[PDB]
Length: 50
Length: 50
Ligand SMILES: [Zn+2]
Ligand SMILES: [Zn+2]
Ligand SMILES: [Zn+2]
Ligand SMILES: [Zn+2]
Image (cartoon, rainbow over all chains, first blue to last red):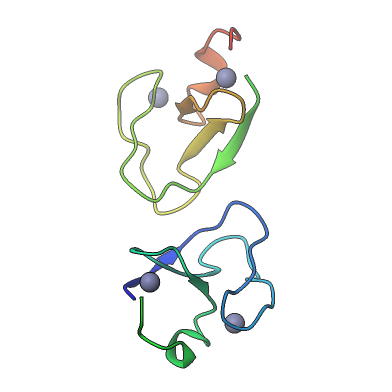
């Protein structure tokens, strides 16, 4: 994965843990290649396989 | 048009005046129906026709 920080325009959940990516901006990280969305706290817990 | 404020993820120009929508977040307004992108200062100068 190549996670880049993303500003989400709709309530989006974290593809790793299932809770909402809270906030107005900078809510999480979106992988540039496959679109997985994760909380900053969950990026490290995701397998690299993309 | 139904302009809603948008957080752009790439350098985007204003479809009304041609200058860059400056900033990291809240750079401009995107029309929800046809995707036109405008600076907050240009929203009022755009014809309504969407
Ligand atoms: Zn990925
Ligand atoms: Zn999470
Ligand atoms: Zn429009
Ligand atoms: Zn403009």
